[PDB]
Amino acid sequence: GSELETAMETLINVFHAHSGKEGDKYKLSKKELKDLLQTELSSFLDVQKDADAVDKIMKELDENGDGEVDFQEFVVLVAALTVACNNFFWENS
Amino acid sequence: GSELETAMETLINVFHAHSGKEGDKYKLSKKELKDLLQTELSSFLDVQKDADAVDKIMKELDENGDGEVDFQEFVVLVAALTVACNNFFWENS
Amino acid sequence: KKAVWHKLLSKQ
Amino acid sequence: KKAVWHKLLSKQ
Ligand SMILES: [Ca+2]
Ligand SMILES: [Ca+2]
Ligand SMILES: [Ca+2]
Ligand SMILES: [Ca+2]
């Protein structure tokens, strides 16, 4: 299929587009990170309604002590909750 | 944007489609893993021309000692080389 | 990482 | 992981 070819195109075009809305051309900040997820990955990744999730994940996801998140750190932890949460589905209701 | 919404759709539809071509409905094997990457992520992820890369990565990527790779293990290591290799680009020539 | 991972999924 | 990572990128 040609699905994966488009997958990479979607991830990076949106990554650098909003990541440089007010911060740096290609570096994320706590404020850029939470807006990018509430934008298209709604109900999948949470950050606005769960405040504990934002400070605990973002501050520790910058495991290097960078109040800014790199693209590599964002894809690993955010993609983990992406497929993991989907598996539980409503079946966990 | 609606790019990320499609991104997840592309990754999973192709993940489970070829992953169950000859192995199990949703588990990867060394043979399913190398065919899935040479299929659409050509020139991005390598496995066929680089034999050392297949046995060393696949056997150690199954860090749990499972000659089969789970979806979570495949997205983390394969996506690393995906954005990493792109950054070097031809500029490393 | 794994220890805190339980908190997010458990607390969610 | 990081130690072997250099081998793949170095050997590539
Ligand atoms: Ca920025
Ligand atoms: Ca960082
Ligand atoms: Ca299978
Ligand atoms: Ca495995």
Image (cartoon, coloured by chain):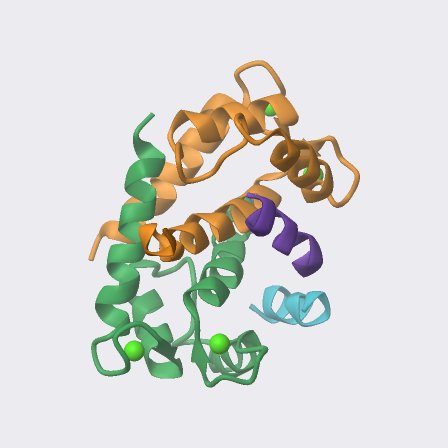
Chain colours: A green, B orange, C cyan, D purple
Which quarter of the image is occupied by the N terminus of chain C? bottom right
Instruction: Residue B63: name its quadrant.
Output: top right
> Would residue A14 be found to the left or right of residue A91 on screen?
left
Measured as percent of width and height from the top left, residue B42 is found at 39, 32
Is residue A39 or residue A62 the one in the foreground? A62
Name of the residue lying farthest toward the top = B22
Measured as percent of width and height from the top left, residue B29 is found at 64, 26
Asked if residue B25 shows in the view, the reply is: no
Asked if residue A19 shows in the view, the reply is: yes
Query: Measuring 34% from the left and 52% from the top, which residue is drawn there?
Result: B89
Measured as percent of width and height from the top left, residue B33 is found at 56, 29
Query: Does A79 sit above or below residue B45?
Result: below
Query: Measuring 60% from the left and 64% from the top, which residue is drawn there?
Result: C9
Name of the residue lying farthest toward the right = B65
Query: Measuring 27% from the left and 82% from the top, which residue is drawn there?
Result: A23
Instruction: Residue B84: name its quadrant.
Output: bottom left
Query: Measuring 45% from the left and 24% from the top, which residue is drawn there?
Result: B17
Query: Does B92 sit above or below residue B15?
Result: below
Measured as percent of width and height from the top left, residue A84 is found at 55, 51
Ligand 4 rendered quadrant: top right
> Would residue A20 be found to the left or right of residue D11 on screen?
left
Instruction: Residue A12: name its quadrant.
Output: bottom left
How many numbered marks have been drawn onto this rendered protein structure?
Answer: 0
> Would residue D8 be found to the left or right of residue A30 on screen?
right
